[PDB]
Every structure is written in structure tokens, then in C-alpha cells.
Length: 284
Image (cartoon, rainbow, N blue to C red; front, side, top):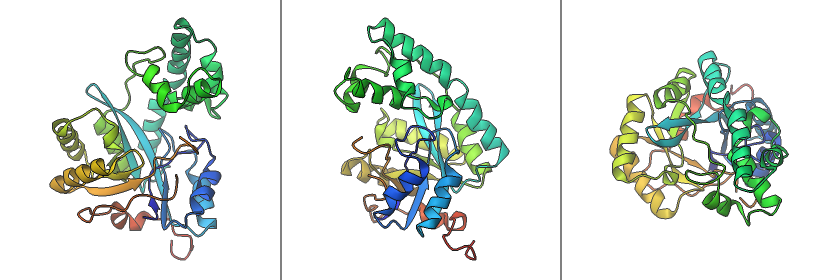
């Protein structure tokens, strides 16, 4: 499929600027794209201009960090108005602790014998307020302390390991509410990544819908075909629309292309057509 509704830019943790990531995706002749940056909308105007220039329909998007019970989940919004005040203030409230968290993550790794990690991570981060674990991981690989990105998180920056600092993000109700209040649709992102059986996934889905959530990512760079299959079933039982995303961050860690949705899925882009920013102006 030529649709990609999940990817990042240097606005938060992607390696490519909004223009660059759009241009990369463009090589694949995509029918639709959505930039969903982590906890910020700052790259949307630039990506929209870049997408328009290449004649590619675009959707304003974002990916919101959520603490649901003991779990961290991600709720993507699609078709949002980034200038809606509640959403903007919402995203800002959850960015607030990132820097202090990152400094502590640096200090934690130092206590564990790896010095210089906050400084090193910051070399990969354009906007300090957006410093994240992905930046730390790029440093650890690049400076040669860790073999690759997968291994970084096996040994570090996750519960029980040096560098991990526990943190509380948005509530599920706030995140879905900000997205829906902004005219968008809320989407449980890359659910295969969560440590959950069918019971937690169902509970998650039920809390999600009660909050106004209409979607879930079925096709994802993070999913195996079995994940695809089973989240399509979860989706159908609860009447959720299916999204698709590459989950692209950087080359090697691809944007503009996803796996065809299982025939049972009701694709979310069909529901978002009125929020799609069309390359032709008269069509907006």
C-alpha cells in the first residue's frame, strides 16, 4: 500500500527534517502521508508545504505519549488542527519534563559507568525540549558504546536498566480528548509493541473508545504479519478504523509505504477525507 500515516522528523526524534522525510517518502509515489511527531506539531506546516509541492495529499498528525496504568502507550491523532488551543497546551504540558528527565537519564548512565550520554544525545537533537531516548540510543551506537539500536534498549533506557527514568505522560482521556477536540481522529499506535495479551488490549481498546477513540494501527513497521492479523480482529470486534504507518525514524533504524491492510479492515483514511490537505488549492 502507498499510504503512510506514521513517521517522525527532526522536530522530535526522526533523523530527517520535515521536508526531507516527505521528499524521501515521495520517491515511493505515495497517495497519502501523515507526519506524526512525538508530543509536538512543530513540523506540520513545513511537511504540508513539502507534500503539496510534490503533489501528495497530506494529513496533519501527531503522536501523544500516554501513561495508562503501568503502561506507556502512544495515541496518534490524524486530521487535527494543530492550532487548537487545548491540544497545543496539552502537547506543551507533556513536553515540560523531557529535558529534566533527559539530564537524569544522562546522570543515571554515568553512575553506571557510561559518561557523557546527555551531551552526546543532545548532538543528535535539534530541539532540546524534545530530547528523547532515541537520541540517547543514536549516541550510544555512534560513540561505539553499543552495537546497534535494538541492543541499546535491551541493555539500557528501559525499566530495570541504567538510563531509564520512570515518567508519567498524558492520561488516555486527555490525549484522545485533545485530538478529538482538534477535529481529528484518535488512533492507538503500533499496539504490537506493548507488553499485553488479548485481555489488556481489549481493556485498552474499551477505555480508548470510552474516551472518544476511533482507530488503531493495524499495518505497522513494528508489526509482524501475525500482529497485523490479530489487531485487524481486535479492530473488527470493536468497530475501529484501521490505520497504517511505517513508523519511520531514520534510514537503517522505510517511509511512504505500508503493508496492504487485511480485507476485513475499514481503512481510516476513508473517514479522514474532509481533513485531507489536497495539493490543489481549489480542492481545499
